[PDB]
Length: 183
Length: 183
Image 1 (cartoon, rainbow over the protein chains, first blue to last red):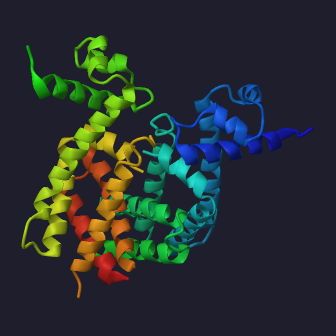
Image 2: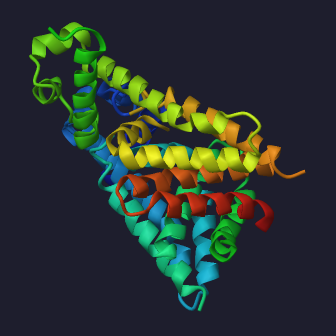
Image 3: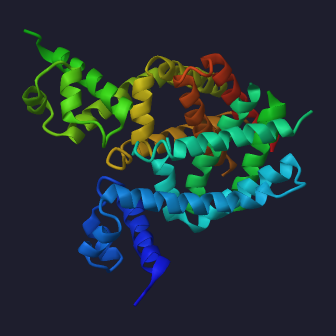
């Protein structure tokens, strides 16, 4: 009769839809319940409020996001190859999971989930400065912040299918090594 | 007994506070009314709902924002000097009006005011590609999007006083002319 993470995954997929479709405030438990084709009373027995569901959804899409970066965390990798693999994983994920990129990029810097993912964002900026430092033997935090901001806006266009992953990863790699060596 | 845009300006300044302090959902008409030191019934006779106030506030801070870009729209200016003047106006505004940058950058890409300022953002991206094109005699929309995304994230650090306007405008100018000529 549909056990564990299966009813779960259906509710979260539908929440993602409605949240990315309409945004947090204009999304309703009503509309999510219809999308999951489950009863509204049912939904509340799992989530209980719109924002609690919004945080579960945010938690889950956040996870797929960092998993997509995982290959960059591989061992023996040159700074360059970590950056390239992260850019490509990030950008490939957005391209395939545009709905979840939208929820995420929104949550980032609503305010409720603006401190889960801004702290995530900041951690990501910190990771980037270290690898930019890990390259050439604080202009570095600064290049990092500019590169992440650039990646965020470019990701938007990748999610909307206006830019190919490769074209996008290409631009971001050289912004990083040539905003670096450039001025 | 305090006539026109004076009661106005007091209510909008206080709304800006509370919205930037707490975010849209966790801001209340309650808290705004206390901040403006006006009665709550009073507030509703001008605004009538939280989001209507939020749009007035968004309208007003959006205006100061584009006014800050105005010197770049001057005549006879080289592409380079338009870009430099826009970067400096944008970044000087964020530095002085951090509360309003926060409301704005949030509204941009809530969803209610995500289509006022995303269309603003997009128009800004379009203006940037044209001047990047107006320089060297669509890699251009693409550099534009990356430069705006970079400016947004850097603006954040400028608003938080972690980066000086000049340092920030410097990095963005060369990202633009060297992500351009770089790869």
